[PDB]
Image (tube, rainbow over all chains, first blue to last red; front, top):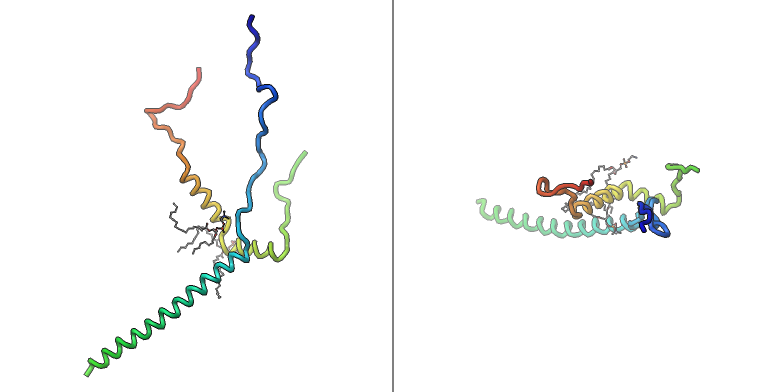
Length: 71
Length: 59
Ligand SMILES: CCCCCCCC/C=C\CCCCCCCC(=O)O[C@H](COC(=O)CCCCCCC/C=C/CCCCCCCC)COP(=O)(O)OCCN
């Protein structure tokens, strides 16, 4: 009492197979990206402004010490 | 039936133009490809340790 056994799909078939493209958006807006860039530029400019003014004062102090020693 | 693989035209609204300009100036799709390669870096390699491991075979 043996029945035919063969490679067949299961009853009801197989599940759906995805084949469509699935490239998502996954990104901010151009406006927001440009805003972030401008903001970091401005923060950097402000920090460099203060630091370079301080460096100019330090250079003036060193030059004054040299002038005092020069004679 | 058939389908067109490249037949779409971009939207010309100011938001879309700015988004494309940001993609041009800020290399968005290039960074996306970088992210894909990094994802593969943190995945597990598919290499078997031959000759101590052998690939599958059949009768
Ligand atoms: C307050 C006022 C401030 C004023 C300053 C405002 C500036 C800020 C906004 C402007 C910034 C623009 C960014 C400048 C760089 C743009 C370069 C560019 O031209 O973009 C690409 C060109 O650049 C490229 O294509 C890159 C190709 C090579 C990419 C391979 C490596 C890049 C991926 C690695 C990411 C690099 C991350 C840099 C990290 C630096 C760390 C020190 C355009 O070329 P095409 O798309 O071919 O079209 C032009 C003709 N139709």
